[PDB]
Length: 285
Length: 285
Ligand SMILES: COc1cc2c(Nc3cc(Cl)c(OC)c(Cl)c3)c(C#N)cnc2cc1OCCCN1CCN(C)CC1
Ligand SMILES: COc1cc2c(Nc3cc(Cl)c(OC)c(Cl)c3)c(C#N)cnc2cc1OCCCN1CCN(C)CC1
Image (cartoon, rainbow over all chains, first blue to last red; front, side, top):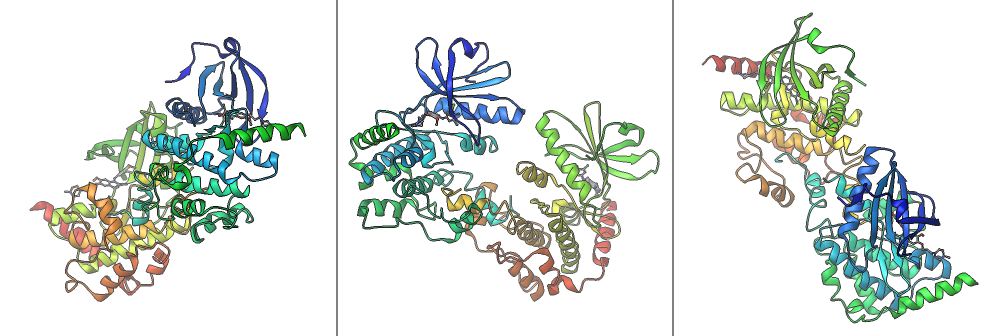
């Protein structure tokens, strides 16, 4: 559909180094042999047919998700058993790594730009009926111009690949409705709210617990709130109050949240350009 | 694992006719060339690798589910592209077809034997961690001795084949718990209760509605009850009251239901032997 097999990628791309290692795999730094353009790349060795079929769905998601605030697909290739996925290199890297490099959380004006830009990307995702299912500061990348790029549509590809009655139990009926409209997309909205807390406090709620307890803690605990409400505005506190609704039916869409005072007046990305400048200067220290 | 490829099935089995047609496929009547034993069979033409992989899981479920009240696997074969699945022929056929042949529901003593035998089979299924996910009168078959055989582990095979975190939405957390112990097995208990109503009234609750409305009707309606409570015992009414608990956490297991007065005193299958005799005599009319 979008994977070019007729053209050899080594006749248009050159690997310049390794960006990241671990978990899902190695990420390489690549440059265009013609235009000189930079791309973050994955040269995945097709082990199983299932693993290959999963990455194709990811490429098809990446190819339709042509939006200012979503990572840009600069090409997908398949030659000599190796699958090449070229994505526009995001110089600032991930927001969680910036917080780690600067040893601090994001300021409220910085969170407001992230939030406003994510809400724009999620509204586009809902229009195309794509659920990200993996929002976190680690999947929000930075450009030098102060704009975010929503990354890693892997969990999205898997939950869409696996997707593609009188005696039914109500809990089964319910889980067939959380895997259907108008609930399935509301998950990313809760995740957005957790990502906002994570950017304000560096760590997500319930980080003090081992990951086994977390699932039961999200199920039984009341919606998470900001540790010091005096350190943040009433608008931020009210944004999380409505976005972190445990009931997905009452929880608003990304379109309804764009009307909230916490993001509606944001006309500049200056706060994030200032964040990227501070992180670059911190590297030289 | 259990599919014999080295031996040709046509050197041990002979097809004697067609039992059923439509939906999932054709079911053939077969006889043993050596012992003369009768088997209901499926000679499925392997179209896709996924369809073939799905039926293998079904055969592996059938092979471990060696129990008096579950259909018996008399062999699985694969030769010249055709997959043969041999199951012990259940002479009385399905309970829903018996109700249709006799133009009536099952009597309460007949329901009590079905219930007691299903609760025995489900208790064995829970011990082996297998969820049927498709209980209905159409999947309860009869022998001439008045015993049931729980059939069609197709939906079980699919929901097990497809089966084989701080930012997660609570509804996603919940659906990851309905696809996990101690909730995932409680679904078959609700289904059992619907099957009991279906055997008492010929039709399952909400049959008057088109199948699109049914999912929302199970979600929003109160637990179903028997149409005429004066026609049934207090024990039957109380059995459905506790088994058809919308909350899967409070809903009992098949082990706890075996202690209920509606099934605990059942020591004979006479009522079902009498049902099979009446259906055979009705055919001659
Ligand atoms: C961390 O490596 C980077 C990964 C990036 C990336 N990942 C990615 C993910 C996946 Cl799942 C893919 O496969 C579908 C593909 Cl093909 C690429 C995309 C995307 N998308 C875009 N741009 C990236 C840019 C990066 O480097 C910039 C960090 C510079 N830096 C180094 C340390 N320091 C001193 C300051 C900050
Ligand atoms: C309706 O055909 C029958 C299907 C049966 C059956 N299905 C089945 C399902 C599946 Cl999903 C399979 O594939 C995994 C396989 Cl291989 C077989 C199993 C099983 N299991 C066992 N025994 C059966 C017996 C039957 O015939 C008895 C009905 C006689 N009768 C005819 C009309 N009448 C005048 C009085 C009643």
